[PDB]
Image: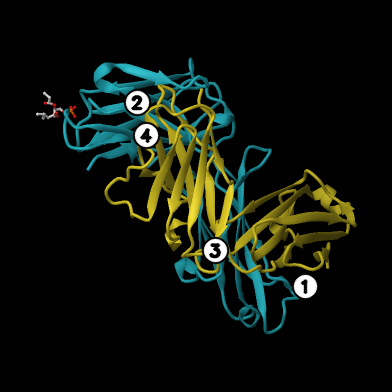
Amino acid sequence: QVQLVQSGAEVKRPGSSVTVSCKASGGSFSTYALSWVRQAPGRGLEWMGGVIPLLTITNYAPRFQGRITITADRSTSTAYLELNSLRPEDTAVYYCAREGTTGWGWLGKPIGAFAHWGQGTLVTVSSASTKGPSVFPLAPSSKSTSGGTAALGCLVKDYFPEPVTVSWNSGALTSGVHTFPAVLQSSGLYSLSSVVTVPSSSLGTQTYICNVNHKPSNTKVDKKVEPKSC
Amino acid sequence: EIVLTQSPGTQSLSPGERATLSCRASQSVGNNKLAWYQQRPGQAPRLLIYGASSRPSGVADRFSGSGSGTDFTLTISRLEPEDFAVYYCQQYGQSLSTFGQGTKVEVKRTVAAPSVFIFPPSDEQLKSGTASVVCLLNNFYPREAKVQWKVDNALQSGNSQESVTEQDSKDSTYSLSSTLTLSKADYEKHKVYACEVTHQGLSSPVTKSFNRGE
């Protein structure tokens, strides 16, 4: 089975250049088409270009023609996507995809469709600097329905870049947990909200701690949420 | 350039039903080089159909492809729980390959009203000079909901951002989070903070509010 392994996530400033790698293992490398497809957050798939390594023939999408460079290195069985003049709208997940075949090696028969995909590579282009988030408590209302259901949570605000992972009570609390997709604020920093609904009866006794983890900034914050003493 | 248009945008169906997705090409797709991909959140796309009708090994037979020329169709004979995802069509009959805008297949369920909660900015955040008011719309269906911010009963606009969760795997509901962002000064200029929620499952708009400092 063909397997594609891409390079790690990238954080770049506007105007710079990035190079994402796609190392192929298993199957044959030279005779099958290797394409690159990007996908902006919450958007669809977009074909950027492709290359047949053994032919040294690359085909680019008109939208990227001039700014993009796709290469194939047969000595390392590794394809490369190079994107220059980066702008904030280039922020996306870049996938490398290879067409499938019916058989093995060079006399394998190509099907054209992208049957094999890489794990994807997050490329974030911004003027913002890498920052750990500030985690504020979304405290449970002091008007929570007695003997009913109350909602509480944590606001993970002003961080860069994506992603952030949030758990509750170190993974012990999973029922009723909603970690929302992050929004990109006008300041250039990300922010998301993670809530959970619990019995109101538990509000005065049970400890609720959200565990916020931001790998890109090496940040780890455990925040305790409790009713406001009003 | 061949432009692919998928229909409909969203397909709301119950498990066990027959799903039919349409892909319409701007011009004839030479050599029927049409493919169907499935993508779930957090994962790469997965090839379902190639050559308009051919199905790779490992892909369930309930997925079938048909059509030619400019009209193509992906058919799921019976909708299983893992089939509710996003589906893309792709043409590769030209040197310039293109994707469709995609179709999301969601679980159709009984209408559920949102549980609305409001959260004032914490003292810790107020110490930093900014104030974030959070409105939570918990577990509702359908996805279409409207959130309106009222400050001293004045309609706010362009100072709030919202995000919606993926359809829940258990109760097939959605949850929405709306954040109203102000400076500490602008926040301390007013008293009444309210979030008004309009939804199909609500006979009348539900308003959750608080007074600053109380």
Q: In x, y percent, where is residue A227?
A: 68, 72
Q: Is residue B14 above or below residue B159?
A: below
Between tags 2 and 4, which lies in front? 4
Residue kind at label 3, given as amino acid type? Cys
Residue kind at label 2, given as amino acid type? Tyr
- Residues marked 4 and 1 touching at CB (< 8 Å): no
Q: Is residue A99 above or below residue A146?
A: above
Quadrant of the image containing the N terminus of chain A: top left
Sequence-wise, which precedes: disc 4 or disc 1? Answer: 4
Sequence-wise, which precedes: disc 3 or disc 2? Answer: 2
Residue A230: give its label: 1
The reply to the same-chain question for discs 2 and 4 is yes
Chain coloured yellow: B
Residue at point 47% right, 44% down? B73
Real-space Cα separation, disc 3 to disc 1, in angstroms: 22 Å
Question: Where does label 4 land, which residue?
Answer: A96
The reply to the same-chain question for discs 2 and 1 is yes
Q: Badge 4, how many Cα within 10 Å: few under 14, some, many 20+?
A: many
Q: In x, y percent, where is residue A142?
A: 74, 74
Chain coloured cyan: A
Q: Label 3: state its secondary structure.
A: strand
Real-space Cα separation, disc 3 to disc 2, in angstroms: 39 Å
Question: Where does label 3 land, which residue?
Answer: A210
Sequence-wise, which precedes: disc 3 or disc 1? Answer: 3
Residue at point 44% right, 56% down? B83
Real-space Cα separation, disc 4 to disc 1, in angstroms: 55 Å
Between tags 3 and 4, which lies in front? 4
The reply to the same-chain question for discs 4 and 1 is yes
